[PDB]
Image (cartoon, helix red, strand yellow):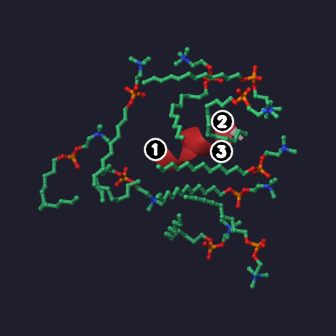
């Protein structure tokens, strides 16, 4: 989901 993409970004 969308928050998993943030974990990737970081
Ligand atoms: C990240 C969405 C937060 C809700 C507010 C935005 C509403 C519009 C987008 C809704 C997208 C659907 O998300 P989902 O696959 O059910 O997300 C599950 C997230 N957790 C694993 C942390 C429970
Ligand atoms: C902000 C919350 C509003 C709630 C309004 C009442 C329920 C509406 C249910 C239908 C919601 C339909 O869209 P969704 O599957 O979530 O879109 C996901 C969009 N992305 C793929 C870009 C993450
Ligand atoms: C308070 C809650 C209100 C509802 C919030 C819903 C947020 C949904 C965000 C969905 C973002 C999807 O972006 P994406 O497809 O990965 O971007 C692609 C970008 N380029 C074209 C430049 C490559
Ligand atoms: C306007 C408000 C925007 C809110 C955006 C929320 C995004 C949430 C993303 C939540 C990701 C959780 O990752 P985590 O495993 O706890 O991260 C660990 C990070 N370090 C390795 C540096 C300690
Ligand atoms: C942006 C915040 C989204 C919160 C969504 C919670 C939905 C329930 C998911 C199941 C419980 C997840 O484990 P928790 O208890 O959160 O422990 C993990 C805490 N960190 C992420 C900081 C490592
Ligand atoms: C607009 C800015 C948006 C920023 C979004 C940030 C998302 C990531 C949040 C990560 C939260 C990290 O918490 P922490 O320091 O390890 O918790 C310390 C307290 N406890 C030990 C009780 C859990
Ligand atoms: C002040 C607020 C600024 C908000 C910025 C929001 C945009 C974040 C964009 C994603 C950042 C991570 O990009 P990346 O996947 O590692 O690089 C490729 C990125 N493009 C495909 C778009 C070229
Ligand atoms: C207008 C609203 C704009 C909101 C923009 C919010 C952006 C929040 C960004 C939060 C960044 C958290 O950094 P972090 O996990 O420690 O970094 C990764 C660190 N390592 C490389 C060592 C793993
Ligand atoms: C892990 C990333 C956390 C932030 C996420 C939100 C922003 C993503 C868009 C990419 C931001 C890129 O910024 P930058 O021009 O290279 O940095 C400016 C600061 N310095 C001059 C010191 C390098
Ligand atoms: C709507 C679209 C707007 C896009 C705006 C421009 C986004 C530019 C993203 C540039 C991302 C470059 O990431 P990188 O330094 O290779 O990896 C991250 C490395 N750190 C964790 C150390 C910071």
Occupied quadrant, residue 1:
top left
Q: Mark 3 Cα within 10 Å, few/some/many (few <14, many 20+)? A: few
* Residue 2 disc label: 1
Q: Is 3 on the left or on the right of 10, as rendered?
A: left
Asked if one can make out residue 4 in the rendered structure from this viewpoint, the answer is: yes
Q: Residue at x 66, y 36 (%)?
A: 8
**SS for tag 3?**
helix
Asked whether the beta carbons under mark 2 and mark 3 sit within 8 Å of each other, the answer is yes
Can you give x and y, in whole percent of width and height, for residue 5 in the image?
Answer: 56, 38
Q: CA distance from mark 2 to mark 3?
A: 5 Å
Q: Which mark is residue 10?
A: none
Q: Is mark 3 within 8 Å of ligand 4?
A: yes
The residues bearing labels 1 and 2 have C-alpha atoms spaced at a distance of 11 Å
User: Element type at marker 1?
Assistant: helix
Q: Are marks 1 and 2 in contact (CB under 8 Å)?
A: no
Instruction: Answer with left or right where residue 5 lies relative to residue 10.
Output: left
Q: Residue at x 46, y 44 (%)?
A: 2
Q: Is residue 7 left or right of residue 2?
A: right
Q: Are there few (<14), some (14-19), or many (20+) residues within 10 Å of tag 1?
A: few
Nearest to N terminus: mark 3 or mark 1: 1
Task: Specify whether tag 1 is near ligand 1 (CB below 8 Å).
Answer: yes
Q: Is residue 1 visible?
A: no
| Mark 2 residue crowding within 10 angstroms, few (<14) / some (14–19) / many (20+) | few
The residue beneath circle 2 is 9
Mark 1 or mark 2, whichever is nearer to me: 2
Which of the two discs, 1 and 2, labels the residue nearer the N terminus?
A: 1
Q: Secondary structure at mark 2?
A: helix
Q: Quadrant of the C terminus?
A: top right
Q: Is mark 2 within 8 Å of ligand 7?
A: yes
Residue positioned 66% across, 35% down in the render: 9
Q: CA distance from mark 3 to mark 1?
A: 9 Å
The residue under label 3 is 7
């Amino acid at each position: 989901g969308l928050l998993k993409r943030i974990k990737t970004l970081l």
